[PDB]
Image (spheres, coloured by chain):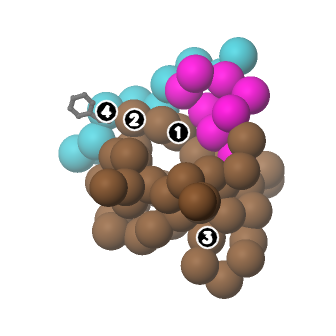
Chain colours: A cyan, B brown
Amino acid sequence: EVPGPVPPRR
Amino acid sequence: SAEYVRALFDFNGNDEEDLPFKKGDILRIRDKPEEQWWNAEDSEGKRGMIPVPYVEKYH
Ligand SMILES: *[C@@H](C)c1ccccc1
């Protein structure tokens, strides 16, 4: 995972 | 006066409503229902949600 994790939804 | 963003990372899309894209893609911002999740539209007219930390404010 090069990019960080996607942000929390809602 | 449309609002665009440039994709910094490749996003395959996790959900069915998500808009997948590739590093360098220009996306037009249509909605901002959340601080970190915006509704965008790609060059071909496909719409969907995108994670803000994966894109940068174009220009
Ligand atoms: C992925 C979005 C990433 C990479 C480095 C630091 C923070 C996030």
* Distance (Cα) linking label 1 and label 2: 6 Å
Q: Is residue B28 above or below residue B25?
A: above
Q: Earlier in the sequence, mark 1 or mark 3?
A: 3
Which of the 4 image quarters holds residue B25?
bottom left
On whether residue B38 falls in the magenta region, the answer is yes
Q: Which residue is mark 1?
A: B51
- Indicate the secondary structure of the residue bearing disc 2: helix
* Distance (Cα) linking label 4 and label 3: 22 Å
Residue B35 in the image: x percent, y percent? Answer: 58, 21
- Residue contact at pointers 2 and 4, CB within 8 angstroms: yes
User: Taking B44 as reference, is B10 left or right?
Assistant: left
* Distance (Cα) linking label 2 and label 4: 9 Å
* Magenta stretch prevailing secondary structure: loop
On whether residue B50 falls in the magenta region, the answer is no
Q: Can I make out residue B9 in this image?
A: no
- Indicate the secondary structure of the residue bearing disc 1: strand
Span of residues in magenta: B32-39
Subunit bearing disc 1:
B
* Depth check, front residue: B12 or B27: B27
Label 1, ligand 1: CB separation under 8 Å: yes
Q: Which residue is mark 4?
A: A4
For the residues beneath circles 2 and 3, the answer to whether they share a chain is: yes
Subunit bearing disc 2:
B
Label 4, ligand 1: CB separation under 8 Å: yes
Q: Label 2 crowding class (10 Å Cα cut-off): few <14, some 14-19, many 20+?
A: some
Q: Which residue is mark 3?
A: B42
